Length: 220
Length: 219
Ligand SMILES: C[C@]12CC[C@H]3[C@@H](CCC4=CC(=O)CC[C@@]43C)[C@@H]1CC[C@@H]2O
Image (cartoon, rainbow over all chains, first blue to last red; front, side, top):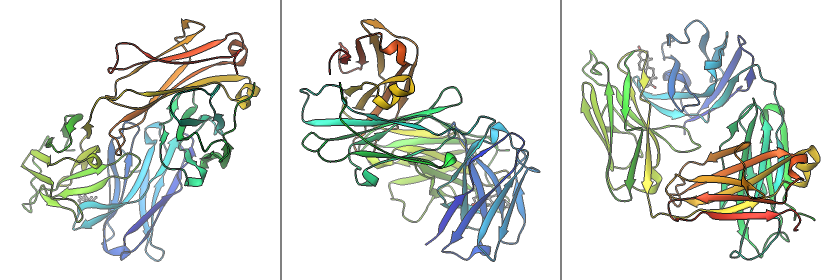
């Protein structure tokens, strides 16, 4: 089974450098063409670079001379060296393997998010969201968590360590003042909470933040 | 640089119907070797793009026969027969005959379903936040269709126009609906100076807004 995994993304200042990694396995490494593709905020995809079986590398005008793709055959690691970074470089970076003979991008990794900015790294604040005064309205209670004021992206959210998956809604972060804000909600049966625990697990890799906020009934 | 133009940017389709996406290159995609490296991809919300079709009409292992591709030179098409909910996401066509290889801007496939009113919930500021000297009132508008909806905030009767942030989730595969978050943020001081907080949802399914609110004097 083909498997590609990216890493190394994070926050970097304008004009800076960064080297991304992509660990491959499941296929003979030096036989196929490996590439780097990126996706910007507007969800547009753009080829960044490729290195074919023979060794030749190829780049696009927007990046030639700043980005250098290379592969470590002994370790099955594909690299992408970035230098003289620009705000436009901000995006999700995917490594992919061709199907065969320069045909298609058959296998993609999960992608590592690279943010180019001068803004300072900032931990998110997680706030529990509990009803204010219980009364009527069916038999299902809705709860939430407000992940506010962090930078940069991304942020991970789960409920009860991933055990609570049904009826969950996690909204995309919104940027305002160099800071991001996101929320998530989970709907459970009234017969459960608060006697049964409901906790949101928020993770923000850039600042090494990992918080488990338990939803508790609001006081007076 | 072969500019690949994709249309529409968004395409509605009901379950079991057919949908077609158009992809056109500013130059021929036919290569010297006689091949045309035109491909199609699908990226579902929160996921990586996936290969569907390559060389105009060749289906990648795993892709259902419902997906067919065709065209030539500069005009290409992706047809999706008997549409299912799981087919939603953004489709992209790709050209690999000229370097640099390029992608089209993408087409978002929306699934049509019965109209559904949002399930609204309002939440007062958490103790922890108040302690920080801040106060955000959050309103969830869950599982609705169509996507267009408006949220109005009122503090003690008057609508509050500033300090609001809204966020729509992508269409959900399980029920073909959408969800939205509305957050009203003020300082702790200004918040403790008022009593009632309400958020009014204006959707197509009703001529009168759905309302949710809480009074601070209440517990
Ligand atoms: C990126 C790619 C592998 C690298 C190929 C690219 C097609 C165009 C191309 C022409 C070349 O001469 C070098 C390899 C490249 C740059 C292929 C498109 C799909 C495949 O995965």
